[PDB]
Length: 158
Ligand SMILES: Nc1nc2ncc(COP(=O)(O)OP(=O)(O)O)nc2c(=O)[nH]1
Image 1: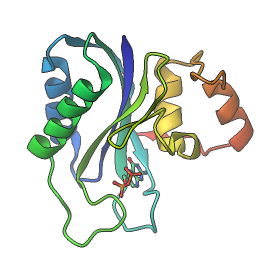
Image 2 (image 1 turned 135 degrees about the horizontal axis):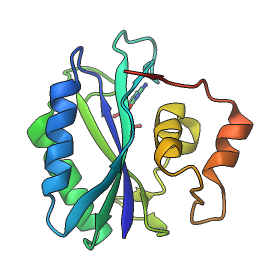
Image 3 (image 1 turned 45 degrees about the horizontal axis):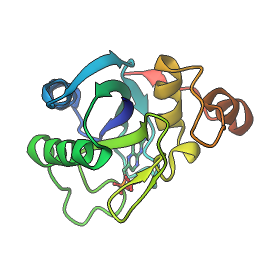
Image 4 (image 1 turned 45 degrees about the vertical axis):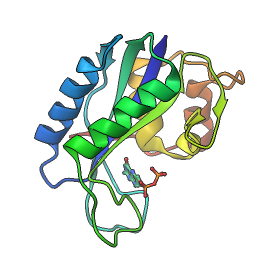
């Protein structure tokens, strides 16, 4: 199954974390990275907060069940990032979000797939569009269309 995972890091120098996360993702059992988008520097979704994020999208081939994949992404979040105390927006330094899991729709207490807000987030959509420009969401929405319509600022590469 191809899962699309968004990586966000709000570290000032996120490359090493992102690389650790990518390695970690590549190490998830039953999985392997198909493609990694470029790394993009994106303005934080919250206030300015300050920290730009590095955002990237990863296409991960996996035979894992989505909740099993989520276990691994959450593990990697815990292992490779930490919590920003008191931060309401982006408390984690490293977010790994399953954006899409194959063509599955998942609406469980643990997991909302497609990612519950990705259609509002250029920082998720543009990297994904880089690696999956033709992507069609389970409901038939098209990634390209969402971008076309919402006119999300293009992202600068990190
Ligand atoms: N530019 C940018 N801004 C961001 N703001 C918040 C989060 C994650 O915020 P969080 O409080 O964890 O909430 P959620 O992941 O549920 O949207 N991620 C980004 C990101 O990846 N890129």
